Length: 269
Ligand SMILES: O=c1cc(CP(=O)(O)O)c2ccc(Br)cc2n1CC1CCCC1
Image 1: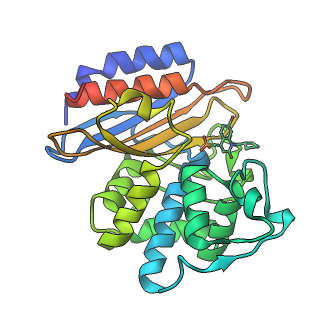
Image 2: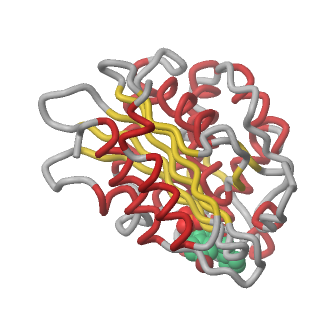
Image 3: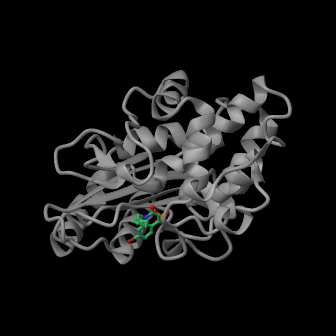
């Protein structure tokens, strides 16, 4: 609740050094204690929607047996920049399960767009988020246009608090059936793109699943994670940044430092 104040001045100093805005929401699932800094502001999702995309695919797999094993074929024209798995299987195709793992663990853009098409596009993923009680999340566009991160534009945004609340529901709550919940957790744990973000703030003997996002403009980048500290209940957190100038650079170091301050606020140093 009021752990925010153990670290509200440290967050203001971090954001001043960064030269932009940092949004943080962290929840101790044991006590319900929370740390919030700009937790209600909108930040561009960038690639961070791909974790929710995989969760929506897993949800649909509860109603559509065989969905995950469905082979998907795609042409050269489906490849977009940063498609490091899907480019290796262009001549063969991949299963829905494989595309979901590529979208989560490599942030694969072709895979993301192919899975968006299966769900009925950005409105389809937005519908899934509404179905679990998230009224903040909006996806509007596809890869790569959703990365514009225009100041003041609500398109393709959510808030750190809504991302944390939704992540808790999907990974630890009852939004997915048990097998689907563990598959989502296992994809997040195998992510390869987040070593310099939240993961950099967590001890090596704690389990962590995360999903990154990097727009590449307006100092805009983010990460959300579930962390299993030993001997206590899991922590769910979201760290989002943006900056006023198109040329402003994101900082992975600032996201790690924000994650450290959120864990210090919850008393999990
Ligand atoms: O779509 C992505 C995906 C990633 C990996 P994540 O978003 O951090 O999960 C990414 C990473 C660093 C940076 Br700079 C930019 C990125 N873009 C936008 C680019 C503009 C053309 C090429 C893709």
